[PDB]
Image: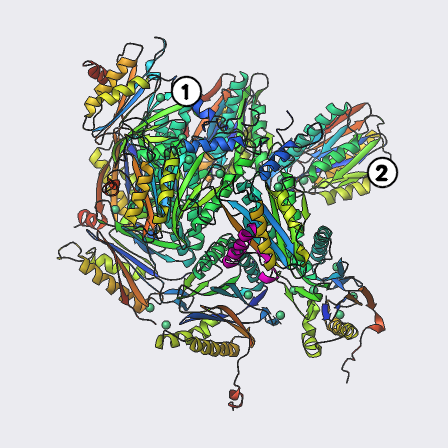
Amino acid sequence: MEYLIGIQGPDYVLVASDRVAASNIVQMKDDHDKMFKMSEKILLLCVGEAGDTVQFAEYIQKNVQLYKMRNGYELSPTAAANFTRRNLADCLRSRTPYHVNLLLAGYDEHEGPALYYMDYLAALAKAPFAAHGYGAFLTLSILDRYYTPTISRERAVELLRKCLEELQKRFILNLPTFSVRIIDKNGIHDLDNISF
Amino acid sequence: TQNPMVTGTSVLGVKFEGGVVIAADMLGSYGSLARFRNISRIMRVNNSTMLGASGDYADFQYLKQVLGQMVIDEELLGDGHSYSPRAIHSWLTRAMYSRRSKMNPLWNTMVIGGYADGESFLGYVDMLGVAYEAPSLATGYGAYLAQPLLREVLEKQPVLSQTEARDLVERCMRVLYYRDARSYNRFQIATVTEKGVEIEGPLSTETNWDIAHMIS
Amino acid sequence: TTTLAFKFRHGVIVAADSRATAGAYIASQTVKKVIEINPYLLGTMAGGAADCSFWERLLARQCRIYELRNKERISVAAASKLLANMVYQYKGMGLSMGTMICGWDKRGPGLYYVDSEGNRISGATFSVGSGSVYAYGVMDRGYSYDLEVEQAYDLARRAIYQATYRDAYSGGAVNLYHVREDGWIRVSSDNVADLHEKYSG
Amino acid sequence: GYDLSASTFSPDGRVFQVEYAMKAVENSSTAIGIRCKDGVVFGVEKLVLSKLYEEGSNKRLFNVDRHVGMAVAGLLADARSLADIAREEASNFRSNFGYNIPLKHLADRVAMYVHAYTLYSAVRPFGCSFMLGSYSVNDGAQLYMIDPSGVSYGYWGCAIGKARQAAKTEIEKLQMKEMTCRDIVKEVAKIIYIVHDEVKDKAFELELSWVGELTNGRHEIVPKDIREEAEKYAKESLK
Amino acid sequence: SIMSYNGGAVMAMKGKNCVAIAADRRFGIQAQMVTTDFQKIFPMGDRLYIGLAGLATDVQTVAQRLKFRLNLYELKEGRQIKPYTLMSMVANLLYEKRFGPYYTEPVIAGLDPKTFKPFICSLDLIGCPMVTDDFVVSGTCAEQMYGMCESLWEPNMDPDHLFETISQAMLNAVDRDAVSGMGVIVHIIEKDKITTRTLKARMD
Amino acid sequence: NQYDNDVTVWSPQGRIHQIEYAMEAVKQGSATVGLKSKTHAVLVALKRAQSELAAHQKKILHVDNHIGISIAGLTADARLLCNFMRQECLDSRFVFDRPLPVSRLVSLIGSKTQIPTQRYGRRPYGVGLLIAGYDDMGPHIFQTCPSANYFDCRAMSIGARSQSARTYLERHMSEFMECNLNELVKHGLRALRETLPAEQDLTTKNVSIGIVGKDLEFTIYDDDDVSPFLEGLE
Amino acid sequence: TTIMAVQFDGGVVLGADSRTTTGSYIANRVTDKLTPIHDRIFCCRSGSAADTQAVADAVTYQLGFHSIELNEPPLVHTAASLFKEMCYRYREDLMAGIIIAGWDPQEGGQVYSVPMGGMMVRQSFAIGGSGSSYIYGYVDATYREGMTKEECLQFTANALALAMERDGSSGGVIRLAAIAESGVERQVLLGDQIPKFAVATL
Amino acid sequence: RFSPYVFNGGTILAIAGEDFAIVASDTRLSEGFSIHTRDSPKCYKLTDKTVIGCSGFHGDCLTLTKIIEARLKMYKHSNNKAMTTGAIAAMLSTILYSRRFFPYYVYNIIGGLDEEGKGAVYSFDPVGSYQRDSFKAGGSASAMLQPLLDNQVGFKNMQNVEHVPLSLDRAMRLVKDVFISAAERDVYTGDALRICIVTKEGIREETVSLRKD
Amino acid sequence: DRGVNTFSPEGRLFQVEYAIEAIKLGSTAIGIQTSEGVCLAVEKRITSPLMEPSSIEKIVEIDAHIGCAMSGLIADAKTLIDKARVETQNHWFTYNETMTVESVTQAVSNLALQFGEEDADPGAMSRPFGVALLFGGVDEKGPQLFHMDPSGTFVQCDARAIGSASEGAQSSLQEVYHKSMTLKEAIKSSLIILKQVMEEKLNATNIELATVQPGQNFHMFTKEELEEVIKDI
Ligand SMILES: [Cl-]
Ligand SMILES: [Cl-]
Ligand SMILES: [Cl-]
Ligand SMILES: [Cl-]
Ligand SMILES: [Cl-]
Ligand SMILES: [Cl-]
Ligand SMILES: [Cl-]
Ligand SMILES: [Cl-]
Ligand SMILES: [Cl-]
Ligand SMILES: [Cl-]
Ligand SMILES: [Cl-]
Ligand SMILES: [Cl-]
Ligand SMILES: [Cl-]
Ligand SMILES: [Cl-]
Ligand SMILES: [Cl-]
Ligand SMILES: [Cl-]
Ligand SMILES: [Cl-]
Ligand SMILES: [Cl-]
Ligand SMILES: [K+]
Ligand SMILES: [K+]
Ligand SMILES: [Mg+2]
Ligand SMILES: [Mg+2]
Ligand SMILES: [Mg+2]
Ligand SMILES: [Mg+2]
Ligand SMILES: [Mg+2]
């Protein structure tokens, strides 16, 4: 059980993900990264079945980078989200479906920040905030309660923390640390891990 | 075949000095129904080799078609080489194993009898490609009812005359008629010697029912 | 089975037991679970013996072709990725493989866990196999990056030993290897019964 | 030039590649077939190009089914290929329909195969002509001949190869409708000896086969003793 | 049920020289709402729309692949597609997947591009078409929708009355379905304009 | 000219020039001899060495326990055909648990090699073989040709100046059936020696020998192993 | 279904009931289960109606073409062989129990069974279908070597009537065909023409 | 539902000496509660230096040994030398793994001489996992044989006994004893014991009678 | 114009004969086999001082016990060398042993004559390879040198030159070769011969040399090791 979260402010998208790789009753890695850089202003966050998750995300990543090399400019976040969706949907009924749940976060020069949610069935929804994993059941209502559309990034990192503190308090799984990144006009920034 | 349809019961064989005898009743059963009461379950393959088959009779007819055509093809060449009993047994082992491995067996258990270069040949092949040779063989219920009698005689006297082997086979066929509910009292005996393959039939066993009056 | 490995200042320690079972029957006590992929790379065997040995042998073939074609040794990252990409195609068909790919390349000591479920992860320490939970307890309480070489040998040895004691499916001998910058070495092979006499009386 | 492909007609409507294949047949030594009251007899003038060869090398008579013989002239590798096609056709017919292939049908089927090699730049015509012979109580004696164009007809007597005309002239003298296979084998040997050019080609073997009432409808080699008497009759008749 | 995994409801209704089409706004996964602005109705022409309920992924795929085919059609033919022809195009697309269907049951609403006659229809997931002269419904609350439409619909409604009727039919139907709602969007299609409204609606 | 480039083009004389040309590849190969008695089949081959420091080309190849071949013509075509023969032999033992009769294997060669003579853009095999075998019908020597024809032989020679070797073989062939193995191999060597320029001789460097028979699986003799056979010649 | 055919000197008699059921609903009470395959060759069909119609159509095509190519009337044995090849090859995808019967100038009147599974056997007389179970005793006791055409038609009608009384899956009318060098003669027994055997009342 | 496998019984054993290898098997071929034949050995000569023992599903034993026979010849043809014991073992691993998803139901043990002339035993699972062993039992009675060999050849659980090299004479006596013990308790092991001894001089054969019940 | 699989009246394939003529456009390579190992030596043939001489690789490792020298159309040699590398690794995979020099050479030579245009896959080989190869290595037969040309004919040689001055170089090889010659003598001899036949003045940058010995693996001589050997010559 893996957790992803995104929160879109006016000019930025904040994303976080747990850093655990688990197997059976053990955590096998405590500094795992569930984020994939697609381009200077796009992150794909990918969870789900082992093998499928990295294979799918890295395929998308290489194709996004290829588009940049072929054309001299990048796909927009929206175009990248639709490209991702097309591939997942096209594989749904094939001999090689990918059992993956995703967020795509991006910043476009002209359209601003965008956050997209996709499930393994390949339904795509744009959202102001979203979360995947069992931890979403405990945190989405906190986001519904405290969010606003104009939420500043200092305040957004607090809101994120409340979600993460709620997992420490109430969720049955041990998820002690989280990767945190923010995207804006100036590209992808690493923030400090949030750790307990 | 996934589901056998019309089937044959036991086939027997025994080696003797100068040849091999095989026997099989002339019945195709359809479940419990004794449906086709005059079918031959024995094939002359060529001058040195004969075959008897238990199990699905359609699948036997297919093997007979294929094998018969293989022998024709070889005879056309007129080149001094013929398939030996052992070669035919090998081919059949491969054919059954190959069909087993495609999960589409030929639903048969077979007894190959032959005589070539002064040696009696007697070989078994089943639907899974299990194959071996022995001085006597019995498929189906024959494995339980006839094979013990065959082996008991062979232990006292490993080399039988033709007539001794023939009488022993008749005794086994009688037992099978008494105790296999899918048997029938009309059978063939096929013999291979130096002289070739002879199929005799239809034959019947005498039976005794005195025990019917020995209950009270 | 119990296998483990860990990165530290002086390379990567790799250790294993030697037991194979078929149900409850002990089929062998002399299995070589540390697979010599090439002189600078080790793999480990857990799950299905044939599955690990076959696919790591194919890995060895491909790494050598790589070296011939490119005129340099493959990285631990790239080797582990080859293995992951080979097995991924067979997910759901019942392969059982849990392996650690252990080396030392331009990024220093390297350690990846790779399995038949599709996982491929880099890490500081891992244990794999039916006895892994028992090895983790002991390894985790003693592990540091700054372990001296002899302290690292002792920890690895003891963690496998303790796993063999609790885990019915682990036993035999503990085999220990050390990946150094100029290649791996075989460090020791100690029968569990002889280790028992040592760690008690 | 109009003669390089079987897919090109000449301006007069000829297919020269088929005619050239026919020239290969016409260069070969002679084979004959004669149908009679109770069967069909084949004979071949089999030129021996080296005394190093075994008696029996490069047979020009084949069994194509148990009841069907085939006699060939022309390029021998092509002829053997056709004997295999004929064998396969006969075998497939038995598997599919459950009885022995009628001779006329076998001839028609193999002729259509030969014909298929006369239409295309992708393949060349067969450089052979062949006869097929059979006997059964139901169908009587039958003798067919097929050429490189794929034409197939039935015959009382037939000859193919370089002395074809000379052979037909001799066959025409026989009242074959009233003669038995045992009578006819002698006449076949006689005719091969008549048309053999002993100055221009030095050594030959006579190859003989037959199918008829006397073989129970099986195509067989003529027994050695009968062949040797037939040769002695032919040699003495040449006097 | 595969068809209830995302929930959702669509309906179309005929008026005098006008048609209406409506949909709920919820995108959810079983019990969990994920967004409340999910698009289920798509323009296929200036006066021709398709509404899709069912599995959200297939709602999106069918809309996109249909648009692909329609764009090519219009480029080749040099005209706008007729409503009946769009229906046939959709039927063909769905039936191609007869043995592994898309889980969506579309409704179409529009006016003929040359005559402006009203058209409505629905299709099942394998492309069986049904044209009506009143209303069509599709979704997890079809029974609730039938009950409202049967009771409220009348022939030859003007655009204002059509708007109130389709709106009341949707709002009251989805309010008896756990997995449909979170808002209602309504398009009224007339010869000279499209009017798009979102309704004041329950958000539970 | 217009009739000589395509194996699908008959000439106006009823010939196929591409087949004739493929046969020239065999006539220019180094000579090899095959002969038989009632109990053994023997191959003898002259090996060419390109230079004084090269090993001498292999001429004799193993096919199965009961069959070997000597080659003349294109080496790569010889390997291709030898691999086909090997596979046909293996298949026969796999299916029937008995050796493939030699005459049946030669038939298969004839059929396989005829195919490319009749299809546009294919070519004949540019190799001739001598095939030594032993089966239920005894010893055999067969010859195969680029034309796809084949011959059953009392003895044979193919390759450069093989007419000489053939003349020797005809001269002595009435003796071969009753020869012991030693005598038979000597005959093979004498025949092969007829192909050589007057100065040159058979040596352990240029002679290769293959033998199969009633009691002897197909065996190749080269280099020091041919010495026993070369002594007490002349 | 009940089907039957019987050999006489110079021809064959074929017969069938006329009932086709889906479950225990009678979907056709006047089915024609005797299908012409060539001028003097018929088949009696039992098992899946779709399967037997499809196979009969295909054999009719194959045999027609064969017969034109040979310029001769087809052998009954050839027709049976064609059925057998298809029924055996596709035995895992067919539910077809066939009787082939007819006349040809080479072997006269002949009856072949091709039961489920695709074996083939020539018989003096053959029965099949669900209702055949109930008439094995009757046919075994009643059959006599050397029956005339008029006797064979009676024997078939009687056997089919008995089967039809007892088998819920058989009934309706009795369709009969006699085939000989002279041709095919078809008739139907219906109502009171069907042989009657009392219920054993009291 | 057709099953493509049946169990046919059989016990196999191999022992490596300093200059010999032994491969041994019983000769009973079984099915269910029945004996097919009392004279079906489970050992196959591969080369003058290598024998293989095969038990399990007889259909697969027969196919697999024929495949190995073909492959040895193919190797000899392409490389101009016989395959070594080690190379046979490596190859067999790959043949077994080619059927990883429809396995050969065969337990294989190779015994032979290595390239220094020393005894070599390789043991396999059905999908081709293998290693070199000093001794190994396989098949039906393997759990009965293996502990005694551990004790008597491996000296396990024994204090104050000299670890001497294993003589051929003692190896033969052990082989006969463990099979006789197995014939008492494993219903599938019986009739006769066939023993192949591989040394520099070649392969020789002994047979010993076992109980026939 | 005629097909690629056309025989000449002399019984040769035109395309193969023409490929053999292409070998003569290649730079000279020499192989010598001794009881102490084999050496392979090749003229680099530098065409501009701006070209990096280390990017000319006309001697390559096939496996640790086998090297290969090439002459002719060098780009053609890549698929051959790769096939040799892959075959040796397949053999190791399957048999857990090193493949013989003869066997590697045989495997590569089976690709020669696999060309033609109606029979094969959509874009199969249209022509033979314009390359000759010297395979030098050590296996249980000891040190061995094999030569292969575009006909697919391959043969063991005690010493062999290939490429433009191979006549010439082969004559000198006859003169100097003997069976008991040491590896160090063979190395000296092959550089003396290269020095004669090369148009440019021989130095430590415009030749390559490699050895394989029973002792040790394939070894490419470094610049400094070449300089050392070049002093005497
Ligand atoms: Cl019957
Ligand atoms: Cl028979
Ligand atoms: Cl160990
Ligand atoms: Cl690579
Ligand atoms: Cl990682
Ligand atoms: Cl494990
Ligand atoms: Cl003519
Ligand atoms: Cl589409
Ligand atoms: Cl040559
Ligand atoms: Cl060549
Ligand atoms: Cl010729
Ligand atoms: Cl010649
Ligand atoms: Cl019907
Ligand atoms: Cl039936
Ligand atoms: Cl039936
Ligand atoms: Cl029925
Ligand atoms: Cl009815
Ligand atoms: Cl050169
Ligand atoms: K009824
Ligand atoms: K026992
Ligand atoms: Mg999957
Ligand atoms: Mg609701
Ligand atoms: Mg709610
Ligand atoms: Mg069906
Ligand atoms: Mg007992």
Q: Chain of mark 1?
A: I
Q: Quadrant of ligand 4?
A: top left
Label 2 environment density (alpha carbons within 10 Å; few <14, some 14–19, many ≥20)? some
* x, y percent for residue B31: 59, 68
Residue C7 sits above or below residue I47 on the image: below
* x, y percent for residue E174: 70, 40
On the rendered structure, is H149 left or right of A79? Answer: left
Residue F6 at least partly seen: yes
Residue F121 sits above or below residue D231 on the image: above
Disc 1 with disc 2 on a shared chain: no
Q: Tell me, yes or no, whether the highlighted magenta stretch contains residue D218.
A: yes
Q: Tell me, yes or no, whether the highlighted magenta stretch contains residue D228.
A: yes
Where is the N terminus of chain F found, in terms of image quarters? top right
On the rendered structure, is D141 left or right of A23? Answer: right
As rendered, which of B33 and E193 lies closer to the eye? B33
Picture disc at residue H58: none
Residue F99 sits above or below residue E42 on the image: below
What secondary structure is found at the residue carrying circle 2?
loop
- Three-letter amino acid code of the residue under disc 1: Glu
Residue C74 sits above or below residue F150 on the image: above
- Name the residue furthest front: D239
As rendered, which of H92 and F47 lies closer to the eye? F47
User: Label 2 belongs to which residue?
Assistant: E154
**Bounds of the magenta span?**
D210-239
User: Label 1 belongs to which residue?
Assistant: I21
